Image (tube, rainbow, N blue to C red; front, side):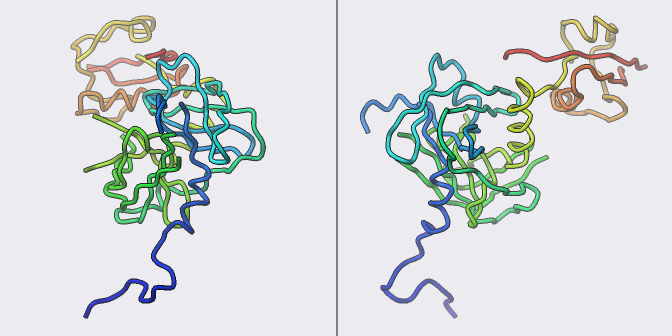
Amino acid sequence: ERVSVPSKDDTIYSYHDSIKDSIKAVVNISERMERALGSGVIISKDGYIVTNNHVIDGADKIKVTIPGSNKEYSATLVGTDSESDLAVIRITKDNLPTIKFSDSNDISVGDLVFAIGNPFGESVTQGIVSALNKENFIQTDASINPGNSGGALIDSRGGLVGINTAIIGIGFAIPSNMVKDTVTQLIKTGKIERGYLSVEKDSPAKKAGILVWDLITEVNGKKVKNTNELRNLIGSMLPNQRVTLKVKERAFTLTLAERK
């Protein structure tokens, strides 16, 4: 019968101990005068900060508010891939709190996870990993709100499992591997390299081809029966690459993407 909880009045189940390590990693990236955009996680000890692209898009000037008193460190966009909905910011600042290895593969449905956001003011909302997809997504029931969005979703050891992403109960974060993958890609390459190509009009499928019949079943041998299940597939195939299968078929040499 029953089960557990801490029994005495000595202390009580404050995840605070495990959270506040990574809560320090979560920065506001702008309680009256809250025209703040949302949050971001300082990923680099040195200065780079992951966040959503939607947190930054449109913003003519980014001021990043840190967890060590409200000193708005100014930020330049390291890189913005909206398809991934991630974005990097640098602030010129010290050995800042880093993110962590949360292997997005290693996390599973029911992993205690905390969406830490900074919408000022640290803000942690707790839930569990609700779902895991591919497109590549953590659904979680830690209140993912735009204030929280771009901040960290973290497993109970404090490790970044996700970077929170606001949308539209169910809250989504971008897997700390898809973040790692694209955040490293963003520190390196300007944005996330991925190439272009029901169908429409542009070059690469015209610059090196001319797709007849409109619906392209497979993409380089891989079947695609789902509307924009190719926007991910063709997106994957790093621009400058060649793609196949046309639907009847033909092969293309594609090119770089765009500013959405």
